[PDB]
Structure formats: structure tokens, C-alpha cells
Image 1 (cartoon, one colour):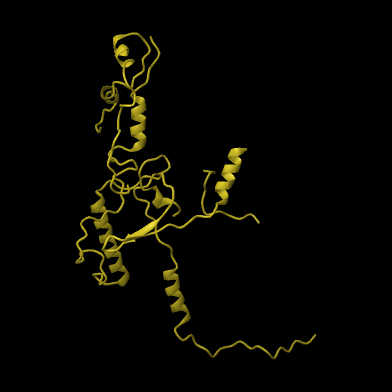
Image 2 (cartoon, one colour; image 1 turned 120 degrees about the vertical axis):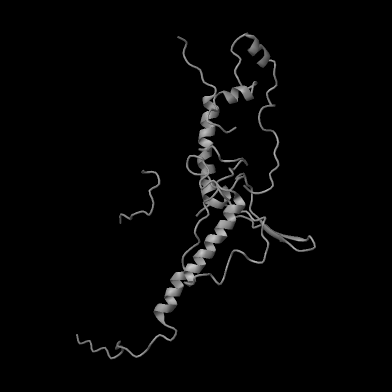
Length: 49
Length: 140
Length: 49
């Protein structure tokens, strides 16, 4: 596998996050902040070219 | 040089040496082969869930079946695999028929597409039909 | 919609889809139509895929 569970309808994503809730409605969102990515930077560079 | 690939992609004086002497005299105390055979049981990665996913052409791959029925039969198949792996006639650790009522669970299947409709007709045939509806030919 | 024959059905279901080449009465109707009112325009998605 690679990227395959993200193909399960609505692939138009922005960022990934996983969360749960307690019993009293309080939740805990965890959003990992991505670093800059080399292949996407190269795709933007060759798009400029 | 010239490394192979797993998958196709695009192209279709005197040396007395009194130090060491390696013969015998220590046995493996939990057992080398047994502990490493457990390790290569545990080494294998997870098998993929390619159900309800687009293929190359765009059609959702997998069999046409209800989502909840596919989840329940998938728990059944896991119970039978657990029975064959513990080598009993019944898996003692069972995944199905538990005390938890789980009548709302859904595992992905080939019934539903990405937009949200059914797959009685695949997406390639649906697109080809919707564009073959409007054609025009030469006059006689 | 399912069935063995699905050719005529798109033209029957969507009258504003055809082109307007001439000053026939059918095209006189279709050229007097709005265009953002065809097909799907609303859904209620509750589960991921």
C-alpha cells in the first residue's frame, strides 16, 4: 500500500488529522504539521519552468 | 551494477593464532530458530484494503455486495483464518458473534463509488454512454 | 439509470443539454433556457465513501 485508503471517496483533502471524543463531548484534535516536501517543491519548480 | 526491479511500471610468516577456536559448547537458551521464526511470523506488513478504491481506468474494484454484509463476512473470514492458525475446529479468540452489538459497522466495498452512487454499471461504461448519447453523423 | 438501453435516456432526461445549431422551434426553446440547472445540485454525504 501507499496512498490507497485516501482513495475512499472525497480525495479532495487538505490536511490529515485524527481525533477522539470523551463521554462528556470534549474532544482531542491532533493535527501533525507537515514539513516542506521535496517532490512537490520540484513539481512547482518545473511548473514555473 | 544493473539492478533488477520488483515491478513493471511504464514498460508494459607463521600465524599460530592462539586467540580464537570456534567449535561448540553453548546452546541457545530460548532457542535461536524458534525465536527468530516467531520474529518472521511478526515481520510481515499488513495486507492491503483495496476494496472500494479506483483502478487504473477509474472503476471501483471489488465485488458488488452490501457494505455491512461485506464487513460481517470479513469478520467471518478472519474468524476462520484464526481457526486455521490456531489449528482447532473453532477459533478460541473469535472476531464474530461477540457480545457487542455492532450492527452499524461498515467496511468498504465495490458497491459505492467515490461520488456516492451505486456500481451496477461501472464508471467507464457510464461515461461512455453519457457521451455516446450525443453524437452526430454525416448526411447521406 | 440502469437498464440495457441507455442511449435515448440522456437526451430525454436533459432537454437543456443539446446544442442549438439552427432556428428550429426546439432550438428556439433550448436557446431560451438557463444552464446551471441541470443534473445534480445537492447531496447529503454522511460517511466516507
